[PDB]
Image (cartoon, coloured by chain):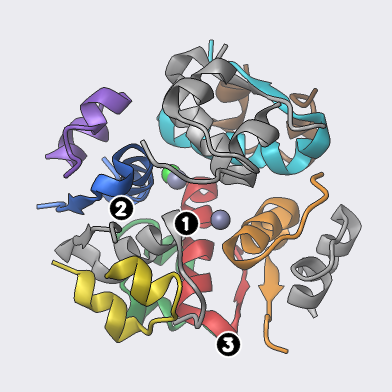
Chain colours: A cyan, C blue, E red, F orange, G green, H yellow, I purple, J brown
Amino acid sequence: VNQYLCGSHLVEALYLVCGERGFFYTPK
Amino acid sequence: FVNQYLCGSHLVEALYLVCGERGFFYTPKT
Amino acid sequence: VNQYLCGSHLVEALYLVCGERGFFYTPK
Amino acid sequence: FVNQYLCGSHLVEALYLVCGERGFFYTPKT
Amino acid sequence: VNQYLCGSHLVEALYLVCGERGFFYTPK
Amino acid sequence: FVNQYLCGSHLVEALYLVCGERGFFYTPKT
Amino acid sequence: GIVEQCCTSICSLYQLENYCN
Amino acid sequence: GIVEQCCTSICSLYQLENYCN
Amino acid sequence: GIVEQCCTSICSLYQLENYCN
Amino acid sequence: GIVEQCCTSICSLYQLENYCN
Amino acid sequence: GIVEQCCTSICSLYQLENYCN
Amino acid sequence: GIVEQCCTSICSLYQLENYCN
Ligand SMILES: [Cl-]
Ligand SMILES: [Zn+2]
Ligand SMILES: [Zn+2]
């Protein structure tokens, strides 16, 4: 549906649960 | 673009905004 | 579509890219 | 309403929330 | 429509307007 | 999960994220 | 609840204040 | 000044409403 | 306005910078 | 990817943790 | 106290789960 | 180091673009 709005929450949700491990963000 | 200290989820959201469809990497560890 | 949710991200995105210049926010 | 220091994007989002469809102005400069 | 995205803004909007009173958040 | 000080709306959004459909309570007062 | 009211139409601070403690 | 009123000093609902349009 | 342009399709920093002061 | 899984249905912390490093 | 446990002290996932319903 | 460049030091648009993919 609306990936740009969804993406912005995702990335906040990964920052919390990955912490010190970090992550990569690839919309593809 | 702003001239400030970007930390925690503010720094990630700045990344999300400026990298666009390239996406980005976030590796905070020392 | 859903301006209130969209609006909230916009205003965050203007605060970052306008910085010291600031902006006006008028939904009209 | 909260009783705290509002800064950066927290202050803008407070504005967005309290001005509603009036919209608002944000002029941070000294 | 999309409660998870909507929910995340709501809870931020309650934190601002309830302040010191706090709130309960029950999606039901 | 991150190892940091969670405050204001960052702490609420962490709650929102980790309690899922249970929902949660936020009672900040002393 | 607040989801079914504030996710469809928009709520104001005053409708929003109904959910506070 | 908004930063001055609400970021380095605290400001009530009535003081943030001065910045509405 | 910016709502009708940046809520439908996505805008970049450069389209976004049109709204600055 | 994570967009096509966590934007349609909701993901939990545990599905979400699949994307970490 | 939530502020006390997670804002002025640090708290793990298991400590934020005490505030769930 | 990203934290090092942008959190405890300040970094311009061109410096955050180094973290894009
Ligand atoms: Cl959203
Ligand atoms: Zn959103
Ligand atoms: Zn913050």
Give the structural element (helix, strand or loop) at label 3: helix
Q: Mark 1 points at which residue?
A: E9
Chain letter behind tag 1: E
Q: Which residue is drawn at 53% across and 10% down?
A: A28
User: Residue C28 location, x and y as percent?
Assistant: 9, 52
Chain letter behind tag 2: C
Left or right side of A27 for C18: left
- Disc on res. C4: 2
User: Residue H21 location, x and y as percent?
Assistant: 13, 66
User: Residue C19 location, x and y as percent?
Assistant: 33, 44
Q: Which of marks 3 and 1 is nearer the N terminus?
A: 1
Front in this rendered view, residue H11 or A4: H11
Whole-angstrom CA distance, mark 1 to mark 2, is 10 Å
Q: Are marks 2 and 3 on the same chain?
A: no
Whole-angstrom CA distance, mark 3 to mark 1, is 18 Å
Q: Residues within 10 Å of mark 2 (few under 14, many from 20)?
A: many
Q: Is there any visible trace of residue C25 in the rendered image? A: yes
Which amino acid, mark 3? Arg
Quadrant assignment, res G10: bottom left
Which amino acid, mark 1? His
Chain letter behind tag 3: E
Give the structural element (helix, strand or loop) at label 2: helix
Q: Mark 3 points at which residue?
A: E21
Instruction: Locate ligand 2 by image quadrant.
Output: top left
Quadrant of the image containing the C terminus of chain G: bottom right
Q: Residues within 10 Å of mark 3 (few under 14, many from 20)?
A: some
User: Residue G2 location, x and y as percent?
Assistant: 47, 68
